[PDB]
Image (cartoon, grey):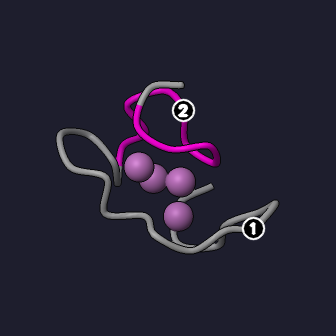
Amino acid sequence: KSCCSCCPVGCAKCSQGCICKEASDKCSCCA
Ligand SMILES: [Cd+2]
Ligand SMILES: [Cd+2]
Ligand SMILES: [Cd+2]
Ligand SMILES: [Cd+2]
């Protein structure tokens, strides 16, 4: 885990702020 369970790796969109709050197995706001 880095930021979320869908972007557990300081994802870009999740650079410095888990701005991804939607993905119960997959997201479409980032990757
Ligand atoms: Cd995520
Ligand atoms: Cd993200
Ligand atoms: Cd996140
Ligand atoms: Cd996302």
SS assignment at label 1: loop
Residue 10 numbered tag: none
Label 2 Cα crowd, 10 Å radius (few <14 / some 14-19 / many 20+):
few
Where, quadrant-wise, is the C terminus in this rendering? bottom right
Q: Which residues are magenta?
A: 3-12
Image quadrant holding the N terminus, namely top right
Q: Amino acid at mark 2?
A: Pro
* Position of 8 relative to 4 (above/below): above
- What's the residue type where badge 1 is placed? Ser
Q: Is residue 25 left or right of residue 14?
A: right
On the image, the x and y values in percent for residue 23 come to 67, 68
Residue at image x 55%, y 43%? Answer: 7
Counting the numbered discs, the total is 2
Q: Residue at x 20, y 49 (%)?
A: 17
Residue at point 56%, 74% (across, down): 22
Find disc 2 in the rendering and name its residue: 8
x and y percent of residue 15 in the render?
26, 40
Structural distance between the alpha carbons of marks 2 and 1 = 14 Å
Is 5 part of what is drawn in magenta? Answer: yes
Answer whether labels 2 and 1 touch (C-beta < 8 Å): no
Q: Is residue 7 magenta?
A: yes
For disc 1, the marked residue is: 24
Front residue of 27 and 5:
5
